[PDB]
Image (cartoon, rainbow, N blue to C red):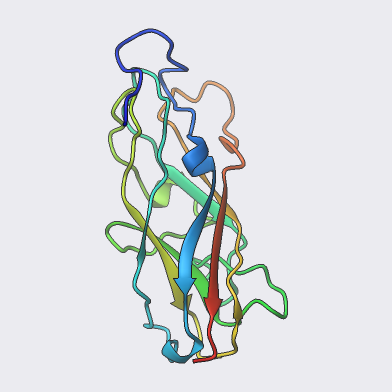
Length: 179
């Protein structure tokens, strides 16, 4: 079942959330990715459903902003680069997007993107996508291995200087088939 503390006792900081284990500490199954389909920069795979469940949360929030940051690729640094090893494929950045299928950069600050009005005390789930972007036509087979974190720039009054919220490590798997 799905039940949570809302408008009741035992709530964390109001302005913020905890981030669930289901979001700070998981793996995206990007399925297979095929070399043979990435034959120009427009090439965009069947965008897998992905979310960051925030819970438990407190009782007073107004929204956040995201802050995704990772190793950005040389080609289009808006795409999350791979582990950068011989066995990681070339010219195939990770394509992390929101439900609007809009390219989300990394090393932007929290200003170039946004978030929804958080509900208090619930498994606050927006809907996002992850898949695999062609930045070139290398079609060298290999595996999918990346690392970033999201921060949430919680709309607290920012009295202390900002940092990362967490080290909520986004890991994505997958496989470039040679067909």
